[PDB]
Image: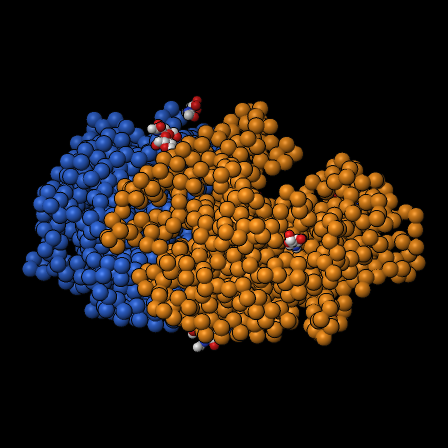
Chain colours: A blue, B orange
Amino acid sequence: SIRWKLVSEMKAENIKSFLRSFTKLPHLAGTEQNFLLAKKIQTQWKKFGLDSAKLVHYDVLLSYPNETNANYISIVDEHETEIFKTSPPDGYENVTNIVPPYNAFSAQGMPEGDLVYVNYARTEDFFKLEREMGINCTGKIVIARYGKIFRGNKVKNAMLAGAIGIILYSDPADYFAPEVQPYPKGWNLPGTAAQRGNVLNLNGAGDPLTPGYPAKEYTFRLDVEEGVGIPRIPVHPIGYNDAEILLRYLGGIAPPDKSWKGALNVSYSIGPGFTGSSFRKVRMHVYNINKITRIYNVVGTIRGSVEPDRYVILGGHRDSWVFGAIDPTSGVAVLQEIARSFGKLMSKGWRPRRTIIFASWDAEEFGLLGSTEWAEENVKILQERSIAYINSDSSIEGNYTLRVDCTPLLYQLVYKLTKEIPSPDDGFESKSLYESWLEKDPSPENKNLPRINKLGSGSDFEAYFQRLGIASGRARYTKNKKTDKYSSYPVYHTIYETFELVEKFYDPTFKKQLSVAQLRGALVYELVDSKIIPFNIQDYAEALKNYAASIYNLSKKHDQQLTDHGVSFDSLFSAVKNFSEAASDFHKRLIQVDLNNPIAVRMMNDQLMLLERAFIDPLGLPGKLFYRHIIFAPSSHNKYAGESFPGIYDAIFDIENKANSRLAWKEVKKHISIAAFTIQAAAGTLKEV
Amino acid sequence: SIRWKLVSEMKAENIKSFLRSFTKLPHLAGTEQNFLLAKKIQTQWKKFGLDSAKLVHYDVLLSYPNETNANYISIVDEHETEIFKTSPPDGYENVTNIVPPYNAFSAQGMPEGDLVYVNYARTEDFFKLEREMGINCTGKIVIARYGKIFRGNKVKNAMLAGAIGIILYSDPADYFAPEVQPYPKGWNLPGTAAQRGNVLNLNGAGDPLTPGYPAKEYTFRLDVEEGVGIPRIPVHPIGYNDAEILLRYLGGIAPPDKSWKGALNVSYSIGPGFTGSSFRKVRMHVYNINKITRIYNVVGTIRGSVEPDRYVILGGHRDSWVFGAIDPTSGVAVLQEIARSFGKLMSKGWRPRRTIIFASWDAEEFGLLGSTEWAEENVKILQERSIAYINSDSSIEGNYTLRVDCTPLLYQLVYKLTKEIPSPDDGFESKSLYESWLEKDPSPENKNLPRINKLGSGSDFEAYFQRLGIASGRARYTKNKKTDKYSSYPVYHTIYETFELVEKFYDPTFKKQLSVAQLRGALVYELVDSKIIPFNIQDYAEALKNYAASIYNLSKKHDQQLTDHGVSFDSLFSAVKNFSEAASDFHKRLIQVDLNNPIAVRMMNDQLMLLERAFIDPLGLPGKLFYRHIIFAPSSHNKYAGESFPGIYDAIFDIENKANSRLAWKEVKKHISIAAFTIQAAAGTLKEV
Ligand SMILES: *[C@@H]1O[C@H](CO)[C@@H](O[C@@H]2O[C@H](CO)[C@@H](O)[C@H](O)[C@H]2NC(C)=O)[C@H](O)[C@H]1NC(C)=O
Ligand SMILES: *[C@@H]1O[C@H](CO)[C@@H](O[C@@H]2O[C@H](CO)[C@@H](O)[C@H](O)[C@H]2NC(C)=O)[C@H](O)[C@H]1NC(C)=O
Ligand SMILES: *[C@@H]1O[C@H](CO)[C@@H](O)[C@H](O)[C@H]1NC(C)=O
Ligand SMILES: *[C@@H]1O[C@H](CO)[C@@H](O)[C@H](O)[C@H]1NC(C)=O
Ligand SMILES: *[C@@H]1O[C@H](CO)[C@@H](O)[C@H](O)[C@H]1NC(C)=O
Ligand SMILES: *[C@@H]1O[C@H](CO)[C@@H](O)[C@H](O)[C@H]1NC(C)=O
Ligand SMILES: *[C@H]1O[C@H](CO)[C@@H](O)[C@H](O)[C@H]1NC(C)=O
Ligand SMILES: *[C@H]1O[C@H](CO)[C@@H](O)[C@H](O)[C@H]1NC(C)=O
Ligand SMILES: [Ca+2]
Ligand SMILES: [Ca+2]
Ligand SMILES: [Cl-]
Ligand SMILES: [Cl-]
Ligand SMILES: [Zn+2]
Ligand SMILES: [Zn+2]
Ligand SMILES: [Zn+2]
Ligand SMILES: [Zn+2]
């Protein structure tokens, strides 16, 4: 078949050569090297035979360290004397433009104060410090370990607590894998390395200065002081050797339980302040600059021969913090190999039914900026014509098995294609990827099917799925979560994401990265070429039954209040019931369609394409204009995680502590009512008359 | 042709019999008689052969007088003694349930104070009273004449001024036609009759308690105190005999110029207070009740044989204040005759290409409630599938010539169809409606084409056009505006809108109402049956060039400020230029389409259908979530009137008096930027690749 030719044409050795070619130098967004990489990708796409490959630019707010006012953290004594102050991988000694560690969009400042350790700086950590312990963060400098929630939420949480700065660091408890050596001898995080990353709280907005509209040359911009999601205290990241020095002499209360204690050789006392030392106060000095900077997406097409006005988007970012060998360059290499293989199909006369859009996004590391501004530019065509979005970010975050996150519309297609891709796993040489994946990660809901996760947030699919309602999917290799308990991967967002890391320690044969390229490519092919779009709406109906039961279960602890405030989930369950009926009836009709009647086929394809759109509410969620998906929009507590019925969940979260209960419960009623309506409206789009 | 059979089948005598049958008794929304009328319409549609005809209900906030606490206005002396107090057409003496005059959704109260005459209670009238004259309305009762702006805006304006009540009345200057007798001898307004009407400021929201979502049984409702657009002072309407008594002894400043002086035999002095009288203070007593009440739309279909998933909506309200012989029942009768004529086509085996939706809306007089709640329910299917909406409200507001208001997409179709409909005008017996209309109302932009107006607001097309972006149109007979200078028509919204009025004084032969039914029906037929949707996008391009020039001209008075604040219209003109190019290229391609290739035809039809949608911004306009059309959304000063580039216009209005100029001009820049983007995005939907 054509799909087998697409998949079998891709080669591990090609992914390896692409990765090596794109990881020799840093390619930070907004810098010359990442523009040069765009031009190289565009030349390659033209060579592969794509119909177009253009650079599309935007001018967006980025953030960089000041090369002549370096950031640092220090400890001073009571006489203001500096007692301690903070200060390339082998083979890259000659590389001159590695950005030092920083947290993009930090406020500027030189705050000084007593230090308080805040664990993960989650909402519950601050609740505990303030409510239980009676500790006052006003005004203190807090130190938090990375993990559990997106780093921007840690900063927002610290701001809410009156902290005047926040230090972030990587605890070996969370980022150091047991019995593996630190880079370069193994793949673990060294004590000298800090994790870069932006600290905006954008909630899907894109460029901070132009929420809702693409950042073109003429475009109105907010004043920088009003930029969406920009924090108002300094934030800076350090490695664990430096963190150990800061934590060592914290006094005050002992860590409250083992869940506060990391792995360094220190007490994990909370503070505030020091005991047993010259160590008296902590200072931060952070002076990164925000500047409007041009960024460049590469956007290419293969136009459909039958439905050129219907799109499947294969999009991945290419900007990195340093070399980004895993994040994102492993996905950049995969995207090139996919485009090469579609070009080989074209060379023998194939053209797809619908149009494929290839996209290499810029400035993802600064808040999904390139992918979001292109969605904002092209919203009117994208919302009326897009079948799906398949991401192409990191392909290789571990080497145990496949992970897939996607809308329930795509579950059946994912299971179908993974059965036709050879497994790359040792011991599965005559078996498919489906078989190895089912063995290694069975679904809790059905032991006979592999696990597929919800799509949440934190990579370029976000605006397409959570704002525009375009069915989306991602797939990558990952770690074994039952045994591997560290966050992300050890060298995430550090200078040590190198080609050598990936080749030596992750996937020496490149077979695992090949399997991810084959699946992302086969997903695009089947969505763009199948006469009938390969979605299954009954799988959405079953997902909604699970999510309704879950939010309802969460409400049982408040059962008396539900009764007293006249709160009922009846309408939600009724909508779910009606959706399941409409989806069953829709599939009964769909098998009867006359495949030789183009308008009959196109009307049913429109219903499959527009089903995800029905869940988008243009009013958004409370305080979040750009999160519109009523089933799947984000975790308010961790942007990386997806949350179901977010309007209901946010309304009921910590409700027992809301000042005004009558008001709080009416908000729960509001969001229940919205979810019921939206699911009923979605069911209505499936009806025949 | 089929269109000629549709048009020639309609009969004046049938419209007359329908009108007489629907105007014997009052049919106020929410009352038994208007439910009975729904059932009669539904029985008729089934008899005519429609595929379906169903009642669709919602439970919405309505407002009625308290039958046991009657409203009134009084004058008292300084001893609190009542000196004056306010208190059926021939042949209707036995009709028992005529609602007395009131303004629906008025606050309740018994305010007492000095009286101030405020002309039309426009923003500029209050500016003059307060800024120029130094008059303080705090706290006064104001009296305003109806006209110039929607009555709800008069009330909002008075509230802003600190007034504690507002009396509305019909001045003969505005509602009494020269040399015609008062009903029953002629068609003029008697001094005893008051104009009913709601006084909400909904800005497109629909039911006040459920903005954004249909008002079903389970639906979350705002507390009534928080109902959208509900005014916070009492409001009540009186006839001019009563107004004369209230105005007569006003003292204080003389009317400032003739534009403040109406036609009664009084001075039109402003007050505050009385001079020359027992007349000391004015009191209002208003105790209407707001109550959630069930309303019923009748919704019927004729399903398409080729594109059943594409819709053309013919919708008109049927609820009236009393008999509503003009408003809306003349349109109710027209809608029935149209449905009858489509049923006759069906009887000979015809079926339309696309689906026609017929709708008889309820509670239009209470804020467009039935049509808006059905749009809110069905938004997901309507926005993805609707070709157009044709209204069917009053057909006969005068007897001089045709008036058409529609999107520029429909201009060419309107001109084409009116050439094939016989003129009903005396002296035009062998001529078409186009010819009589061109002679009587030529367009200012092109003397060789008849005038077509912008669609604004104030009838059931509003949510479809201004929220959802569905191309809309309306047509009716009207007065000669160069000679007839009165507002609306004299007996508008009074008890004197009777069948006898229409038959004796407006259209005895029913030929004018017939011509309106033929045009509304022919519009539906051509939109639903033509293989290629009959829109012209180059007419939209020319309209945008006119609107860009107009808003720019308006800015010239502020030219120095534009320069000082770096405000430019360059991007707007550039977007308009690009749209005109894209529309020209689109039509060049459209004439080449292979009419025998269904997918080629369907892709171009999708572009014609979705063009109006491109102008809808889900973020809305400032303070108005439900006005989304960036070119055509409303006048903030008069909901009946449409305003172009409303975001730019509202931003620049009264700007010289804004407290903060730097902030005010940035808002102008914002709205210019949004308009430029939106027109460019719309152009992008027309592009081939
Ligand atoms: C699910 O569909 C059912 C059937 O159409 C709806 O049930 C109606 O519910 C209302 C109360 O909300 C009752 O007045 C009707 O009697 C019900 N009809 C039947 C046949 O049971 C139900 O409302 C729909 N659910 C939602 C959320 O719209
Ligand atoms: C109208 O289309 C033109 C042509 O594509 C756009 O012109 C570009 O404008 C930007 C400045 O905004 C310049 O950087 C480019 O050099 C222009 N190109 C050309 C060929 O003139 C214009 O931006 C579009 N208008 C809008 C509002 O999008
Ligand atoms: C970088 O820091 C130096 C030293 O404070 C300062 O003078 C310079 O202006 C900074 N650069 C920018 C863009 O702020
Ligand atoms: C890769 O797989 C090998 C072989 O099982 C294992 O020893 C190693 O820890 C894995 N590497 C990573 C980064 O997980
Ligand atoms: C009507 O007014 C009477 C007299 O004030 C009052 O008692 C009654 O409750 C009112 N009806 C309603 C629904 O308020
Ligand atoms: C209707 O037309 C007649 C004949 O021209 C005219 O005398 C009369 O004023 C018109 N009626 C109305 C209500 O305008
Ligand atoms: C800590 O919190 C309280 C209440 O927020 C605040 O009044 C106080 O100023 C804070 N502490 C200090 C030391 O200022
Ligand atoms: C009229 O306006 C001023 C300013 O709004 C207000 O202070 C005053 O109270 C008002 N007049 C009266 C009589 O209260
Ligand atoms: Ca933007
Ligand atoms: Ca509503
Ligand atoms: Cl990915
Ligand atoms: Cl109308
Ligand atoms: Zn990434
Ligand atoms: Zn990253
Ligand atoms: Zn009307
Ligand atoms: Zn009316």
Q: Is residue A644 left or right of residue B688?
A: right
Task: Give B390 or A316, whichever is nearer the viewer.
Answer: B390
| Position of the N terminus of chain A by quadrant | bottom left
Residue A435, given in percent of the width and then of the height, sits at 14, 62
Q: Is residue A513 left or right of residue A262?
A: left
Q: Is residue B586 visible?
A: yes
Q: Is residue B265 left or right of residue A248?
A: right
| Position of the C terminus of chain A by quadrant | bottom left
Which of the 4 quarters of the picture holds residue A596?
Answer: bottom left
Task: Give A164 or A10, whichever is nearer the viewer.
Answer: A10
Task: Give B316 or B66, whichever is nearer the viewer.
Answer: B316
Residue B478, given in percent of the width and then of the height, sits at 59, 51
- At x 81%, y 49%, the residue is B264
- At x 83%, y 59%, the residue is B74
Task: Give B137 or A316, whichever is nearer the viewer.
Answer: B137
Q: Is residue A249 visible?
A: no
Residue A571, given in percent of the width and then of the height, sits at 45, 70
- At x 24%, y 58%, the residue is A598
